[PDB]
Length: 212
Length: 211
Ligand SMILES: NC(=O)c1ccc[n+]([C@@H]2O[C@H](COP(=O)([O-])OP(=O)(O)OC[C@H]3O[C@@H](n4cnc5c(N)ncnc54)[C@H](O)[C@@H]3O)[C@@H](O)[C@H]2O)c1
Ligand SMILES: NC(=O)c1ccc[n+]([C@@H]2O[C@H](COP(=O)([O-])OP(=O)(O)OC[C@H]3O[C@@H](n4cnc5c(N)ncnc54)[C@H](O)[C@@H]3O)[C@@H](O)[C@H]2O)c1
Image 1 (tube, rainbow over the protein chains, first blue to last red):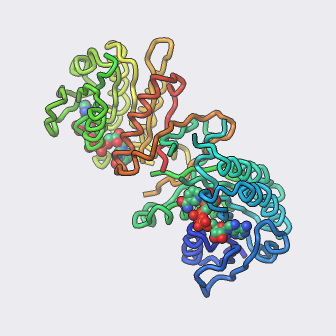
Image 2 (image 1 turned 180 degrees about the vertical axis):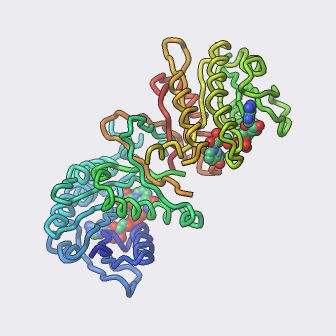
């Protein structure tokens, strides 16, 4: 249960990758998704709508980390869907997380999220409200910790770095990172962030960007 | 003046790439270095140590931007050389920059600077380099400064503050998707310089390079 996590959207492109590395790191992985993927024997697969408490709840029992990288496709231009799943459905993931005793939830956000006050479209708008819900939920004294990892027309090339000692960062070990592709990189950062969150609760409620 | 600029350590691995790209944007480019490296028909080369007040002045005389990406070899293990060049030397670069009416200094720092108090002697001098240069920012004296921190214990993720305290720089990635790691690091240096002369409040800040 210290090595047990659920991946929400575990059938998808990012999800599958997450499953690979979590399994490789000796994690017991549940997968929650509304589509059954390429059968992996070593995974308790649950099928369901992340908007549903009834669907979600059993996939979360016994799990310490939830990975939320489920989403409708940005390309679909289905606004009511984005609204339903990214924005409304997100309150279900957090409350079901608390119900089941999940201790960490790691949201996959967007990098376009950094544009909060032409790249701001309705999808980005839902993902901001998503990140704001998830990082508002951070309650360390109840031992419920959250973060958001933000991977990516318009892109931030440079990000300011606070010199006041307020800047948090997640350390990796280069020897394990060289032969890793773009996604294996994004995925790795998720797993390191989650591991370092049990070791250092002051990362809760922050959002991170990746490098290189 | 407007489109003249000097790369200090312009013969360096990074230097060579900085120079290729400034030229491509139609900068008139000076290189200043202790070694001559590869001849570039379109580049004025001034030989010298960056610590020497007299060597450098003519290399900055009449230019408007300065990219400092000069460093002694990190592998050398010469505690004194590192301190000599990165701190005392850089302090000169800032002097003669002002004595030359230069408007913008863009240092190349180290991402390893973030590891302070959590880690080579080298890195401690980069730390002193950085805060010297950001120390030198003075917008009321027309002398904007910025530092860019290019990347075995490596940092992966970095907090982005939500209250609008932090500043970022936009790039149209549509067109830098066919760059190498270095070409991107450089493109960072240029964008920063370019936008530092549209919004002065990038002065005094250090920046990280993203995906
Ligand atoms: N992978 C990247 O590099 C990258 C880049 C930017 C953004 N993202 C973010 O990552 C996520 C998508 O990544 P992807 O490329 O793997 O997407 P994808 O479409 O390949 O997979 C997402 C998964 O979400 C699942 N899902 C959708 N609606 C669901 C619902 N109602 N209930 C349960 N599961 C549901 C889908 O079945 C799918 O398996 C989003 O949060 C997106 O903004 C990814
Ligand atoms: N780009 C990367 O891969 C990378 C990675 C980590 C950090 N960096 C940073 O990049 C910077 C430069 O790295 P590089 O690989 O281009 O170095 P390099 O060794 O290829 O070139 C640096 C140049 O500095 C010049 N120089 C040294 N002492 C001088 C002096 N006293 N006066 C004038 N010129 C002098 C040298 O002649 C050399 O040509 C460093 O400050 C380092 O922190 C590089």
